[PDB]
Length: 494
Image (cartoon, rainbow, N blue to C red; front, side, top):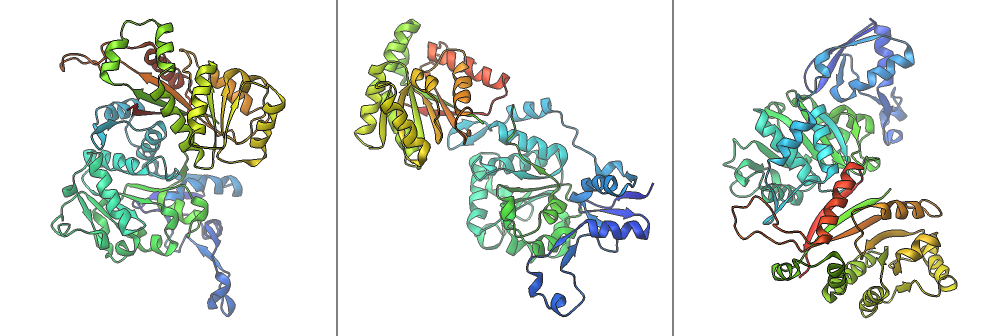
């Protein structure tokens, strides 16, 4: 063929082609330098101001290899690519989930599980070896890094290098790693200013954490020990820095750059892709963001409720003053972020109860179900305009019929549905009819009043389920099947 791409090492692939093909490629893999007008080589020399990532030694940063395909389709060339360049991990999604399920991950003393977008990021990173994980600062990348690092540790012999922006984050990263209980401080060597008085003894630690400023001062050889490398908030990484260590990471089979601000990067996207591989945004589904909140009740309340019919249980829970207070608080909290929330209720005694708690602590609150139109669209317009921190307490009826609702950021289901999720279709519909933002999050409250087993030798979490819990679980299973964007959280009512 015209072009042959051979496996060199884990930092670069090597190209063999005609000298003519070489120069076309050399211009392909280039971009306009930032501030090139201030460079004297440009103003008085022979520089055109572009930077070329493909030098005469014919070595191309590993992560840009997938772009060769595009080069050929654009210049009508045929190329052969060494299969070991596209080698993937022998890891099925089933084994991954199995591995994940057997892990005891914590947050303080509470056992927890990774959100879907976190698992998909880890899985994608792992299977493809090198990738830029495009995720916001929320969505805890901390755990994502810990899982990637954990996997490596259990399957390979090299060390894992993690680069963060500041020394404070150096510490935060380490502390989080132990918090999850996936690593111990003895396994994590902090370098540079983030080091503790005992990091000097940790020469064999499988995990090294530091800043670009420190890492860049290390000798080429030092980099041979890492099999995996990660850079959190990699958009703060400069091309100079990347180019400085790129060649030392020759055995670094796994590389990840994590960021949710790729558009504010010091370096050019091309430079990032060459070092970390292509971009993967987990935010993928098949609009609505669902938050399943497990509201746990006092064990004693749990024991008294047992035996009550569905109709009775709804009466009891819905009328509970503390639950009304909890919801009000959730609403307020959400509004204080200059965001608008919708508190859905069914029975007026409930709605007003909730409305009065809020009002006795927050002004921008509106009750809606009466004066059906004139005052209804009035509010619906106060929101559509651009008001912020507006909590509106309405009934499922109101918001279904007369629609518009633009700036709607949150919808709090104060009256749990049944085992069906149609309400979501409705919310989804109404929002994607007259208004936009459509990235509203729905808070699905599940009232967990399940009864714990007497013995500790019971392999069940609960021995008895109240109805609202069964329903919430039915709803969760439905979100999974329908592959919705959902997350689960637990909170004690008291």
